[PDB]
Image: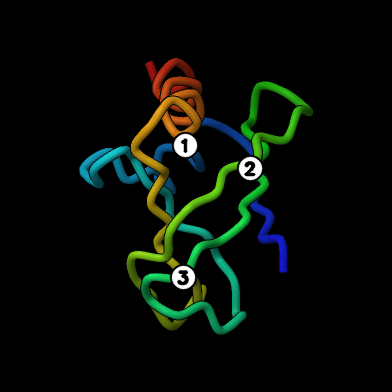
Amino acid sequence: GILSLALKDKPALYSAYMPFVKGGGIFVPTPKRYMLGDEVFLLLTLPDSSERLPVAGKVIWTTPAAAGIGVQFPDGPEGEAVRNKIETLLA
């Protein structure tokens, strides 16, 4: 299914965001069984706007508990927009 994450404030976004992942990435809490390598339809709400950012991400890792997955943003212009919006907010 669609995966959603809403970040409440900048500290939360800072804790979630993984700038070291190529293309940018984010940790997303979920108990759902995503497998490594799967494509994931993520809807991200950032603290500064009601607007949901859709991203076709890739599962790059999983953690148990919260339980969740690391999601890598796509390398091209689709990914860079979400990456840029996050970086602007964290500046």
**Between marks 2 and 3 in the image, the one whose residue lies nearer the viewer:** 3
Q: Position of residue 11 (x, y in %)?
A: 47, 36
**Between marks 3 and 1 in the image, the one whose residue lies nearer the viewer:** 3
Q: Secondary structure at mark 1?
A: helix
Q: Residues within 10 Å of mark 3 (few under 14, many from 20)?
A: few
The answer to whether the residue labelled 2 contacts the one labelled 3, judged by CB atoms less than 8 Å apart, is no
Q: Position of residue 56 (x, y in %)?
A: 55, 49
Locate the C terminus and report the quarter of the image it occupies.
top left
The residue identified by callout 3 is: 38
Give amino acid for label 1: Pro
The residue identified by callout 2 is: 44
Above/below status of 54 relative to 68 = above
The structure residue drawn at horizontal position 50% and vertical position 21%, both measured from the top left corner, is: 85
Q: Earlier in the sequence, mark 2 or mark 3?
A: 3
Q: Earlier in the sequence, mark 1 or mark 2?
A: 1
The residue identified by callout 1 is: 11
In the image: residue 17, left or right of residue 10? left
The alpha-carbon separation of the residues under discs 3 and 1 comes to 28 Å
Q: Residues within 10 Å of mark 2 (few under 14, many from 20)?
A: many
Q: Position of residue 27 (x, y in %)?
A: 44, 56
The alpha-carbon separation of the residues under discs 2 and 3 comes to 18 Å
In the image: residue 80, left or right of residue 22? right
Q: Secondary structure at mark 2?
A: strand
Viewer-proximal residue among 23 and 16: 23
The structure residue drawn at horizontal position 49% and vertical position 23%, both measured from the top left corner, is: 81
**Between marks 1 and 2 in the image, the one whose residue lies nearer the viewer:** 2
Viewer-proximal residue among 7 and 3: 3
> Looking at the rendering, which quadrant does residue 64 occupy?
bottom left
